[PDB]
Length: 148
Length: 148
Length: 148
Length: 148
Image 1 (spheres, chains in turn yellow, blue, cyan, orange):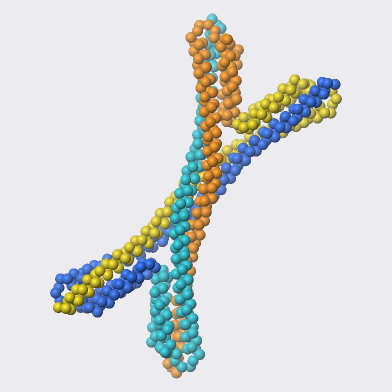
Image 2 (cartoon, rainbow over the protein chains, first blue to last red):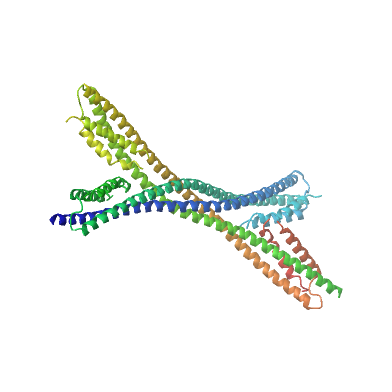
């Protein structure tokens, strides 16, 4: 009678407490697993981002490398031409300073001087390789500059 | 006489203009090559950074993966135990609700109820795996709960 | 008559040569611009990849940091409990070695010994925090171990 | 007597079992904390790598962008000049095809034709901007080409 009433009351209390404990345990398990899985998905996204960036960076590395090598090649070439030009120009100027008589054709000298001025003033803002072609003419004029 | 004086003046002008053009061309070549080389060194640093990050990310990916798998394993296990417990608890409570006479030992019932309360209240902030061991006792008490 | 025929022939030749030069110049301009634009799109993709990875890495950094701090906290705590336990255990063993008469309750001693064995053998593969709760019982048993 | 001998034996067993359990717990705590700390150091290295790469990538992005804009500018300019040239060339060729009498100076026509050939054959491997200067001469020659 009253023993059964107490049994029912206690069974009810245990039912409620057990379902509370059950929901609590399940929620905490789900939450910690969610934290782990979310950190894992973020690490995976970061690794895939690194892989994509590494591919694009092999690409950009090849581009920047061949560009730098191209510029180095053309720069060394035009520096070599510049040094040959400077050598012969110094030679001729020394010949003028040494000899007391005429050494060079004044027409060719004035033309070469004005050409040098034009070239130097085109070099103020465009690239330096747009000048390489003119370095031929200079050479030519330095070769026909002396009286001969 | 004056022809030689004019030759010297023009040679001087050409010397100065040529060295100006020379320094200008060399400076612009050096500057553009410096831009190319600096962009190349930065691209190389970026590629090496991507490689280092990719290695560290393989590492962190393995760590986060085995952690998530560990949590998933233990969570499924404790969920299975929870479902067995809930099954037998529902069975016993239904037996109480169905029969008009006593069904369970009230001492064991009160002990199991208070244990469930203790467990649910330990689960409020520590992990969920620290509870797995207690799930044994619950099971034991659910097996000796009915009058038999 | 023949002057006009030659004019037509030369105009035709110039038309063809001009369209050839035109297509050549346009193709080379388009190709170099394509190289520049493709390297630019790859650099942009790499930068965006780095940004996404940096965000995901702030996330993973926070996760790994709070996990390491949690483990350090609980490890220092359980190490402190272990050192208190070791202190009292050494104290009691020295009391046994020093006094020629009984010092401890043999029942409690055997129970504590078997509990230590159970605990050490559960620690062979699960975490170390699943043991923290048992460290209470040990303490309790070390406090009621001496004859008093 | 024998009670004390048994007490000593049991104290010895408990000492050894306790130090075994102690070393075991400490080793597992240290190992799991080491795993967490190592994953944390790797995540930190990866984040710092991403930051360095992002800086270098802002740099390379600026470089590649200004290069592409420079090429686009000069390409549109030389395309505009090419289209003006093609317009006047088509106009003159149509005048030749329409009128039954002479239309252009044959000397200028032959010179312009050979210049176009030289230019088209220089464009087989160097850049397309090294040609921009010659596009002036062409224009000039197309303006003095007709009999006037």
